[PDB]
Amino acid sequence: SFPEVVELNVGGQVYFTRHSTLISIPHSLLWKMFSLAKDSKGRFFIDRDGFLFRYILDYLRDRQVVLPDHFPEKGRLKREAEYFQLPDLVKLLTP
Amino acid sequence: SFPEVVELNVGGQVYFTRHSTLISIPHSLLWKMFSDLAKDSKGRFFIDRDGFLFRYILDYLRDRQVVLPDHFPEKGRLKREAEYFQLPDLVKLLT
Amino acid sequence: SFPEVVELNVGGQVYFTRHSTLISIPHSLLWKMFSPLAKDSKGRFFIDRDGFLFRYILDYLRDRQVVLPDHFPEKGRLKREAEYFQLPDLVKLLTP
Amino acid sequence: SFPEVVELNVGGQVYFTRHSTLISIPHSLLWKMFSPNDLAKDSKGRFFIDRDGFLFRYILDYLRDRQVVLPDHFPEKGRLKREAEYFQLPDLVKLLTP
Amino acid sequence: SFPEVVELNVGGQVYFTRHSTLISIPHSLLWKMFSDLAKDSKGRFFIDRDGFLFRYILDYLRDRQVVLPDHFPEKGRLKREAEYFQLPDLVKLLTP
């Protein structure tokens, strides 16, 4: 069984989230993953960009994502959204 | 009963605050929460939200006002956090 | 043997990746480095190259394509890094 | 003796490099500094270099490849030439003069 | 006693320099300061001045000359910083 609070390591960046948040969107990558690669400290490892994952996590939490003003990695985040299989997030970052 | 000093884990970022600070604003989310709670591996109360932005949420709870750093790019993201924690006066302060 | 999750130090910048990602492209520098070694004070594997540009090298090793930030000024510097790590397909993507 | 991987602090900016990279160019300043007691160290034990930390990445890149590619519309070309002069890298000074 | 390497905080911007560099010019403000000092929360010596312009003040203390970025505009603002730190030779260099 998975714990209520899941400790993650996304390409070096440590993130904490509820197990419910990870499996919130069915047929997505994280849902497939948590419905495993582990680091030296036992944290679940995701081989992706750690900085962009906070905007992925925010989308999983609210199903909408607010980005900082003058955000230069809109296209890079769209790629991350594609990887985690979040089509509604890809659709938000596309225009 | 809740201790005087409450140890928190907000999406990975550890925060320490007084119990009085959390229940300072009635009918807000944190007030409802601290007046059956998700806990991390180390027993810390877990809040599934952005850890960075929570310091500005805490600052507002301690002073009723919040001073932001120069050229702050996450004004809109903080307004979303204020909405979540149900702090209408903080949302209004972010016009 | 090499662990599943490899902790790296690229000229000061700490990166974490799967061992499979490093040896993903055969006859490349990282493949030569991690297939059968300099370590920092904390035991992390050391590569003496620019740490900032390595995130775009790592992204390419992950997806075989790399998306860059808007108005990216280090396209030429990244092409040099791609040459060093012996990633010809990445050089070909950056060069035109 | 110096370790294989050298931890540096250049005007508060931390850099990591091989010892071989520092002593790569003979009769240069870093070569004089790291060729075999008395070196300046920061509070965390890192070797301290009292120079601009931002420009040092382009100095380090030159020591690695003997060539340096700069970002597009780089405004500190003249300031980097000064840094190249300080570290006694004549071929780098020559590259930055036109 | 002052350490060999001095950690500074000039209006938010962190700078590291040798103690010798600070006291290099006698009868200047920094010389008077480093020959009961304001410190930030992390223990760094605090100077309530513009952090961005201080790198050009530090560079002058190091080389006893001024190398500025290409097309640098804020000369006048740097002259006022030079006046503050009591560096008359630097003021004399920035005048036209």
Image (cartoon, coloured by chain):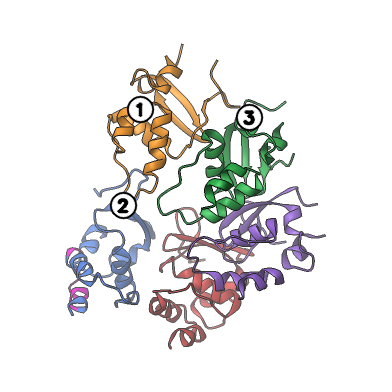
Chain colours: A green, B orange, C purple, D red, E blue
Q: What residue does disc 1 label?
A: B87
| Image location of residue A18, percent across then percent down | 59, 29
How far apart marks 3 and 2 lie (CA) works out to 45 Å
The image shows a total of numbered marks equal to 3
Q: Amino acid at mark 3?
A: His
Q: What residue does disc 2 label?
A: E45
Q: Nearer the viewer, mark 1 or mark 2?
A: 1
Pointer 1 indicates a residue of which chain? B
Q: What is the magenta range? A: E84-92
Looking at the rendered structure, whether the residues under marks 1 and 3 are on a common chain is answered as no
Q: Nearer the viewer, mark 3 or mark 2?
A: 3
In this image, D62 relative to B18: left or right?
Answer: right
Residue B65's tag is none
Q: Amino acid at mark 2?
A: Phe
Q: Amino acid at mark 1?
A: Leu
Q: Image point 35% across, 46% down: which residue?
A: E43
As helix, strand or loop, the secondary structure at mark 3 comes to helix
